Image (cartoon, rainbow, N blue to C red; front, side, top):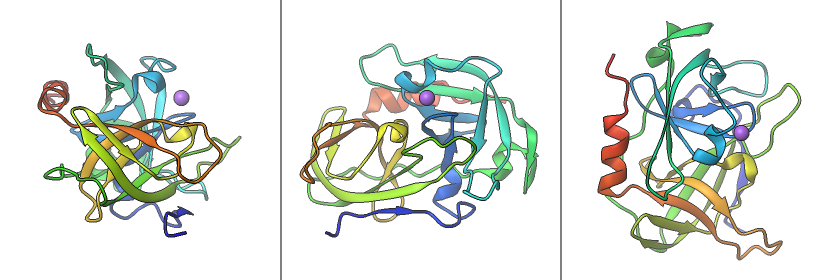
Amino acid sequence: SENQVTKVKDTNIFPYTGVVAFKSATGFVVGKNTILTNKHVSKNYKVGDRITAHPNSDKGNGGIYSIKKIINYPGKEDVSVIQVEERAIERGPKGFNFNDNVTPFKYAAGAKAGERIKVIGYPHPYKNKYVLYESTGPVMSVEGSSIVYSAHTERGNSGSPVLNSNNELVGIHFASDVKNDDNRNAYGVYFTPEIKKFIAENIDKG
Ligand code: NA
């Protein structure tokens, strides 16, 4: 089957440099000192909790950062903006500045049923290891703030970016059908104008 799930060997190149890890799920960078995740992920975390930038399976990462603010979208969609303190609590390879160690994504022009997407995140938490995966499959439908795709995802993928074939952002993963078969739908939030505005409003001003 051409819908594949594979481990990402090196996480220090684009697009993996846009992805972050919480203790047990995923997020991704949207702007200066600012990450996007799901509300069902951010509910587990508080001010002072830590996130790790694109950790690899061999103790390497882009630094460890402290949460400074959590802003939950007041609408129904499963979207949460998290701001971090700019200076790392564990230096990244490109220095202490969060923004020097990570890369935000460009929004795609849109998405259509049938196109290939890629969900990038940490599907399963491990004792003292982070294992980044990429999972591919087709878009099934796009309607309003919903994007549905048939790519394998697990619990830890909550908050993962959903990218098109050219690494442009089409959605944020939040849920999946629990069925055992391969013809299983996964669900993301599609970036409608009011969700894009909410995110833009809540990027750290500096
Ligand atoms: Na979590």
